[PDB]
Amino acid sequence: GKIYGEYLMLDKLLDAQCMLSEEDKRPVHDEHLFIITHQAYELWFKQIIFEFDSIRDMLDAEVIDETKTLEIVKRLNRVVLILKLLVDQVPILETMTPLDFMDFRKYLAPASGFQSLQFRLIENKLGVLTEQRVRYSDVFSDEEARNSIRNSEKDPSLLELVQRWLERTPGLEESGFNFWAKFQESVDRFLEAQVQSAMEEPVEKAKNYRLMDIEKRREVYRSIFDPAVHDALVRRGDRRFSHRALQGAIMITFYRDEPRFSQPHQLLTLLMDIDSLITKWRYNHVIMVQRMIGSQQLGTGGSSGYQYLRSTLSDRYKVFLDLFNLSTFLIPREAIPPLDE
Amino acid sequence: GKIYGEYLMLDKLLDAQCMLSEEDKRPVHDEHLFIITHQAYELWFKQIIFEFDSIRDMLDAEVIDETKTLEIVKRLNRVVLILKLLVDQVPILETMTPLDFMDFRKYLAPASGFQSLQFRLIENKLGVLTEQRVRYSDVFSDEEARNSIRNSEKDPSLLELVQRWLERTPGLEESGFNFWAKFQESVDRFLEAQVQSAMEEPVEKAKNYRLMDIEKRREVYRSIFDPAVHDALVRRGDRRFSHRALQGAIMITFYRDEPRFSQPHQLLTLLMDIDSLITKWRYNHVIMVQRMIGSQQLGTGGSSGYQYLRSTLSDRYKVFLDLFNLSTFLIPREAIPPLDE
Amino acid sequence: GKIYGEYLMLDKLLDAQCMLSEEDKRPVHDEHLFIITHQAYELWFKQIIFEFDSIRDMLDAEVIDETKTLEIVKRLNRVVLILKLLVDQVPILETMTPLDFMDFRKYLAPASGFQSLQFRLIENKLGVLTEQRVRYSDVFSDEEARNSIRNSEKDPSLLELVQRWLERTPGLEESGFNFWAKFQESVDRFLEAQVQSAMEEPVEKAKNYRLMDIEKRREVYRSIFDPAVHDALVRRGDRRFSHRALQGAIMITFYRDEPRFSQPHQLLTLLMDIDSLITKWRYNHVIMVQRMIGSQQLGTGGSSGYQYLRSTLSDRYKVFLDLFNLSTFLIPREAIPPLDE
Amino acid sequence: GKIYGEYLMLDKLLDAQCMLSEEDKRPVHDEHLFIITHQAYELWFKQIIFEFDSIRDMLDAEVIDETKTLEIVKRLNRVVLILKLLVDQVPILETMTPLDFMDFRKYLAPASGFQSLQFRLIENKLGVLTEQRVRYSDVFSDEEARNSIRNSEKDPSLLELVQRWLERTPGLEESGFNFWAKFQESVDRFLEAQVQSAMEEPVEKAKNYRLMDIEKRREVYRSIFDPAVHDALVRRGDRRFSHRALQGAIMITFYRDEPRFSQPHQLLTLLMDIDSLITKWRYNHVIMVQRMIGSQQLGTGGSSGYQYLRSTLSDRYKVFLDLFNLSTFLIPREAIPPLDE
Ligand code: HEM
Ligand code: HEM
Ligand code: HEM
Ligand code: HEM
Ligand SMILES: Cc1ccc2cncn2c1
Ligand SMILES: Cc1ccc2cncn2c1
Ligand SMILES: Cc1ccc2cncn2c1
Ligand SMILES: Cc1ccc2cncn2c1
């Protein structure tokens, strides 16, 4: 179009609000809010997908320069703001009372939140593993929806592309900076100095606490320095990243204050914020489900739905799970290998 | 429809996003965000209108009981939450850079924010007076849009209906409680006691300050006790309310802690919050216009647009202007006529 | 005092910021933010306690009128707003980097979040049961702190006082409205009508699903109509409320649209919002702990602390647990016993 | 100290809450909220000052590297988050009713918001010019407060230091990139091409509108290319920046997408966000003053105070006024001189 409403296709957009309670000559006022709220979510889901696909295209390249990294950071930050808005949309729908919802939920019988193609496309494009999902894709009767999901699982997710970018971190290379080995030998040097300082403790409980603590540190570093331990944790589902991607991620977090790593760090932080905000939506949605129809109601066949949503709050659904635990492996500033390159 | 996407008409809704930069084979990524942002606004504008029209129907009645008042309060509070969300949508669009916007604003030449039928319908249904508007309704080329605006100006606004409800306040009546006269004579009694206390001041500057202050209080009460002064202020545009509606509003604010007036008070407060939040959107929108194209750019013909938006921030656009100044006329708790009925 | 700084005792308040890294001639800039953030929390914790104690005094009375209920609702809503602000304070402290925190966390060795007297007083005054707490009160070395906690556990909590108020609900009484029996017999009448409608189903899978569903409804109502089942669930820790308090709570939620119950309903909703917002703070605090020092760091002696905080997210810490599940027991509007009194 | 309360000096901090209505044996509950709210503001004002002074020290240097720029950006962003929290604190105090405030505002007679030393120190350290202030520093009776303000006006503000940093922008130099001249000659080339395109317009109203518009563009560029026009606008108070600082600011906004300028751009954006958020606090504070005591009340001596606060909303109080208008001078991407260096 050309003028405001023609450009925005308001003739199409504002003709998609059909209250089924109205067409059945028993209108329920808040059903208009129910529709509008979901359509605002679906509009922003399309925007999120559009931004995710553009970030996937920029990450599916041999090298990602400082200019392309800034663009990726901008678009990830935009997704963060849209996710906060989407979390904030819940109290607007929580304004409808359970009895008003009960008077129209009968018209929704075949419909299901599981049938949101865009919500699934978001989960898949970010990296929610099909094997890590709770049992409880085949809900989608349409063939274009099934084809859309097939492509989202087949094509590389944001998790795979970020890992590839993380593995190519300059500075990890043995030929050059050799960060991983410098980190291993400074961890050994630091942890021994901690043993020597604890040996000089005037009190025995304090000497023993420090020594027990150093042993727990030894085990923490063993989970990342022994690749067999890391690869076993990845297999269990406690980690997502490859051993080399984790090395890159750890190096980015160590040198975040350096101009060269501040932007890659921000990209990782926004990836974490996205995960955390999708989890916040899941929680607020399960609180709202509970407020409206409790753990189970007429038509639900028990607390099956409720318990499934409650189970989506687990680390099984966090894509960049590894990013939250990087500070466990941190060493003081004085102990970090200085940058030379 | 029946299943999720058919119920929500996602086939229609998600087919209304046409980037003109894409159809011209010169696509600008952030134009997708520009469209989606406006469509989320337009969806919520429709919800606001739907709630406003339902509140108008409940207020266009002989008596509004405690049950219907609770429903009106709920729906006004819902509009408050939607307005906060709409204010919060601005930083999402402020994520687009001026240079990216400059690469597609050429395709928008005939379009204008003035062509938002729903934004005008919101202003009119709330009560933005046609005579109080800045010079700078005839923008709308379509006949259904012109007819929609004609009806919104003709049919009673939220301002007119609230005034009618306010005029019917029980307790204002001479036959019963006679609040206005009790308020006048307690104002006189309180202000004289203030003169007597100031007369006993040991310091002359303090006695004189108190006496100058009591004189300014006398003039404040004169603007509401002399109907000629109030009616002149309404004529100037400094007030909106009729003299009897203002009496009701003042009585509701005085006895807000009493169960009988707490709900009418909350209705008035939410009416104020709505005004204040529409003003907050106007401000954030003028800040965003400024960030994107400054006070004037190529195609604007000077700072005409900018200065008009900047002028919409004035009290000329506040519908319930009177509601913000009710605390100027307040007297201590000890001086308020006790409720009997 | 009398002037601004003397009234606010800014001489005392702005002399309580002692950076231990500064006194050790190794200053860490963000330690100032660490102190200020905690002091803003402690100031608002004192305000929360002050409001909680005033609500406890109003609830520790024979009858609570409509006027005192409005005051309680106002103060509960104030606590909600302060809790949202406190949740929002986390991203301000998350602005400090893990390496900057690592350079001063050594000076905090004896200090512990467990030593916040005001946080414990908040938990106790709301109603966090001492037996429902995770093993992991005796941390407090001072005698006035131990005496403060002793009194908070001994004196009635907000949970006990709300239950007393809920038990005294007019309308529950057999002598008058007899709500519980009317609810039981309308549940029986409604559930049988649902069996008869399911019997007329043309499809067998649909008839069987409806019948399986009605059986699950029968069991839900059994948990509240058989007092032995409710009393067993209270004993297990799945419920907090007495059988009579639950009856009152259910009646308030059923007739919330009625002027008589809207205010008691709002009080219950704000009580739920408080619980939910304290849970949101706990979550954001465990995310921030994780961002700063992961699941374990030098000095922690393993993931003991982290796992304890992670366990505070369970229903074991939700005081008004029962309030979230009231919609499970809801019946359509057509099936609710009409109000007469 | 060493343990939680000793480290945070909670013995001092939680002993600074003296309600004057309580000491006069006429306690007003919400006076506790009034005190706590102001003390939370004063605590965060101290944090803001601490961050501002550290940014002043980093900016008072010959060269500011990419590493020091990241630190400045981090601390400015922290101030943004604290300012949002401070804006959000207003609705918490707006929870107190005007009648409850009226029962204790008598004890505040000598106190005044003008006596907040920290609020003035914030305004001065940011750059609120003493000559640009409204008539209505000498309020401060204490000598350490007068000395604190004297030093804040004497020592360079954030506005002066940012201008110095902006003037040293590499790329502005004639010897090297010579941005200003390249910008002038590309503006001339672009504006002439616009005349030639308008000359080919089939419609005369369209040709004339385009030509009138190009003339308004010519005048816009004249205000920045003729230093006499810029220096006259600075003198009038419509601009703050020196002609060379404005050149740097314009160059940073033009090449913001380039890695070299993205961080300097972010610093400028956060400086704008700070200005805008202090303005948002001023507005919310004048709305809250109005809600509590209207435009004037007993003790105010008329609307003097109210009108002064209402006048602080003007551009006279915006420190980085110039930053909001930089998009007025923008040219399309195709017209921007390519970077070489
Ligand atoms: C009145 C409020 C709502 C209720 C009672 C509700 C209830 C439910 C229930 C019971 C489920 C489980 C499967 C099913 O029966 O569909 C579900 C899933 C879902 N709903 Fe909602 N919902 C509400 C509002 C919303 C809104 C506003 C959205 C946003 C678009 C939404 C999005 C979803 C999604 C995406 C799922 C999938 C859950 C996941 O796999 O993580 N719901 N909902
Ligand atoms: C890129 C950001 C935007 C820019 C540069 C912009 C610019 C403008 C300008 C210059 C005007 C004056 C008349 C005209 O030329 O149309 C205007 C008016 C208006 N715009 Fe925007 N706008 C933006 C985003 C939005 C958004 C997201 C909305 C929300 C739906 C919106 C709604 C309106 C409305 C309703 C008016 C009427 C103003 C009033 O009468 O108070 N604008 N806009
Ligand atoms: C730099 C950020 C912070 C870190 C790393 C941190 C870490 C921790 C840890 C590890 C614990 C477990 C016991 C202990 O070692 O003290 C804890 C408990 C606690 N912290 Fe924090 N904390 C941080 C900030 C805060 C803030 C800003 C507050 C607010 C006043 C706070 C309040 C508490 C409270 C009240 C507990 C008790 C937890 C409960 O029983 O639910 N913490 N913190
Ligand atoms: C009950 C709410 C409040 C009322 C009625 C109120 C009223 C006023 C008034 C009338 C003035 C003008 C001079 C005077 O008489 O002091 C003023 C100034 C001021 N107040 Fe408030 N105030 C309130 C709350 C606050 C809060 C919570 C803060 C935050 C610390 C604050 C900070 C200030 C500051 C800094 C000024 C200086 C204004 C400027 O120069 O821009 N006020 N206030
Ligand atoms: C339309 C619709 C139906 C069911 C549902 C569940 N969660 C969101 N939903 C939306
Ligand atoms: C589509 C469109 C065009 C112009 C405009 C101005 N303010 C919002 N707008 C939206
Ligand atoms: C001072 C201090 C020490 C330890 C701690 C843990 N969570 C908050 N904390 C505050
Ligand atoms: C204590 C106090 C007195 C007066 C005042 C005005 N604005 C904030 N204020 C605070």
Image (cartoon, coloured by chain):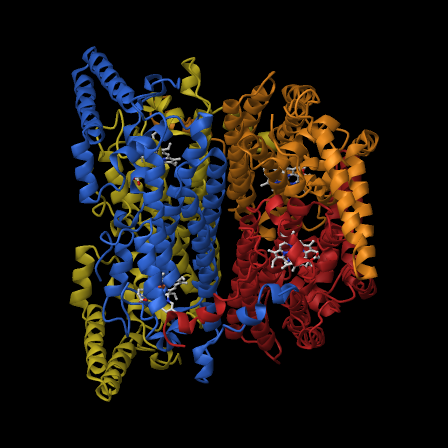
Chain colours: A blue, B red, C yellow, D orange
Report which quarter residue A291 is drawn in. bottom left
Q: Nearer the viewer, residue D171 or C53?
A: D171
Report which quarter residue D256 is drawn in. top right
Residue at image x 33%, y 78%?
C176
Ligand 3 rendered quadrant: top left
Residue at image x 62%, y 52%?
B104
Residue at image x 16%, y 38%?
A232
Considering the image in quadrants, where does the N terminus of chain C appear? top right
User: Where is residue C47 drawn, in percent x and y?
Assistant: 45, 42
Does residue C53 show up? no
Does residue A123 show up? yes
In the image, residue B87 sits, relative to residue A194, either above or below, namely below
User: Where is residue D96 drawn, in percent x and y?
Assistant: 55, 50
User: Where is residue A65 drawn, in percent x and y?
Assistant: 46, 34
Report which quarter residue A134 is drawn in. bottom left
Q: Nearer the viewer, residue C238 or A10?
A: A10
